[PDB]
Every structure is written in structure tokens, then in C-alpha cells.
């Protein structure tokens, strides 16, 4: 059986892959009440139990997928979890390329880290991250917009 690793990037912000997202017991142990599913094809796990608030960012792992368009919507959901003292899990698939992009963007905007420091911070807690040059380029443009206040 799979040992579910729900990585706490921040005490209320967790990152995982598709198999980590299927462990209901771990999610309730960690006081998680919000889930962001960054895939088009995965089910919203545990949906039928009425335990969590869900948000789907229907993105693919392609070199042309636009994730920047979903940043603000994801940040608003994370902020709602933060304000009510609940944890939020963001997940995609094995290499966590999609979900780690949104986590890093949140750290850049709301923790005021640089892109590099945010990546290193996430990488230290979640060692296995599949690179995506397209998403990396979007984070670099996101950093410049933040540094310019746009
Ligand atoms: C976000 C900046 C990534 C940077 S800045 C300098 C390096 C890297 C880096 N990142 C990765 S994985 C991270 C991603 O690509 C996302 C999360 C977008 C999916 N693999 C290898 C390297 C080599 C060195």
C-alpha cells in the first residue's frame, strides 16, 4: 500500500501527487478542508463524502499549458483556507510539476520570496519535482511583474 506523503510547505499548505491525495485519514489528521486539483482528468477525490471544499484548475503538463491565468484564483482559495485556520492541499500527478508551480507562485507573492528561494524552499521539502521549462518561464515573468507591482 502507498504511504501518503502530504508535504507541509507551510503549516496550512500541503503539496502532493495523485496517490497522496487519496488518503482520507491523513487529510483529516492534518486538518485539511480545502483541495486544489490541478488536472483535467483526475477525479475530485473524496468528493461524495462532502468533507472538503474543492477547486479544479484544469491544466495539462504540456509545454504550452498556461498556468499563470490560474494564479489569482488559486491564491484566493488559499487565502480563504488561511483565514479560517484550515489546511489546503494542492496536488496533480507524480512529478508535482503543476501543483509545485502554484505553490512556488504563492510563496513569491504572499511570502515575498524570490523565485529561486521559493523553489529551493519547496525542493528542500519535496525533493522529487519534475522540471517544466514552460512553467519555469511563467514563474520568471511572474517574478518580474511582482518586482514592478503589476
Ligand atoms: C522554479 C525555478 C526552477 C529552477 S531555477 C534554477 C534551477 C531550477 C531547476 N528546477 C527544477 S524543477 C522546478 C520546475 O520546473 C517547476 C516547479 C516550474 C515545475 N529542476 C532543475 C533545475 C535546475 C536549476
Image: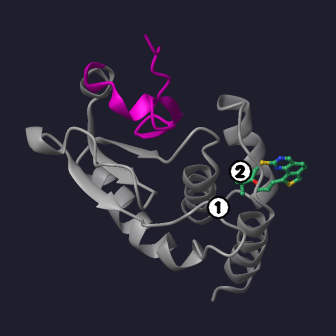
Quarter of the image where the N terminus is located:
top left
What residue is shown at x 13% (from left), y 40% (from top)?
51
Which mark identifies residue 118? 2
Task: Please give the range of residues in magenta.
Answer: 1-25
Query: Does mark 2's beta carbon lie closer than 8 Å to ligand 1?
Result: yes
**In this rendering, position of residue 85 left or right of residue 61:** left
Residue 129 at x, y percent in the picture: 71, 41
In percent of the image, x 63 and y 89: which residue is there? 150
On the picture, is 42 further left or further right than 86? right
Dot 2: element: helix
| SS for dot 1 | helix
Mark 2 or mark 1, earlier in chain = 1
Give the answer, above or below, for where 2 lies relative to 102. above
Residue 58 versus residue 124 in the image, above or below: below
Q: Compare residues 44 and 85 and report the one nearer the observer.
A: 44
Of all residues shown, which one is farthest toward the front?
Answer: 41
* Residue at 37 percent of width and 53 percent of height: 36
Q: Which residue is mark 1?
A: 108
In the image, taking residue 54 as reference, residue 100 lies left or right, namely: right
Marks 2 and 1: CB-CB under 8 Å?
A: yes
Q: Is residue 89 one of those drawn in magenta?
A: no
Amino acid at each position: 500500500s502507498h504511504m501518503a506523503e502530504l508535504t507541509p510547505i507551510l503549516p496550512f499548505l500541503f503539496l502532493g501527487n495523485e496517490q497522496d491525495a487519496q488518503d482520507l485519514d491523513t487529510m483529516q489528521r492534518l486538518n485539511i478542508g480545502y483541495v486544489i486539483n490541478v488536472t483535467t482528468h483526475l477525479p475530485l477525490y473524496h468528493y461524495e463524502k462532502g468533507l472538503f471544499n474543492y477547486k479544479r484548475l484544469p491544466a495539462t503538463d504540456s509545454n504550452k499549458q498556461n498556468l499563470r491565468q490560474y494564479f489569482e484564483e488559486a491564491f484566493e482559495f488559499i487565502e480563504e483556507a488561511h483565514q479560517c485556520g484550515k489546511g489546503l492541499l494542492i496536488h496533480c500527478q507524480a512529478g508535482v510539476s503543476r501543483s509545485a508551480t502554484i505553490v512556488i507562485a504563492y510563496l513569491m507573492k504572499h511570502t515575498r520570496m524570490t523565485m529561486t528561494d521559493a523553489y529551493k524552499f519547496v525542493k528542500g521539502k519535496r525533493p522529487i519535482i519534475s522540471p517544466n521549462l514552460n512553467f519555469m518561464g511563467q514563474l520568471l515573468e511572474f517574478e518580474e511583474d511582482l518586482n514592478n507591482g503589476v
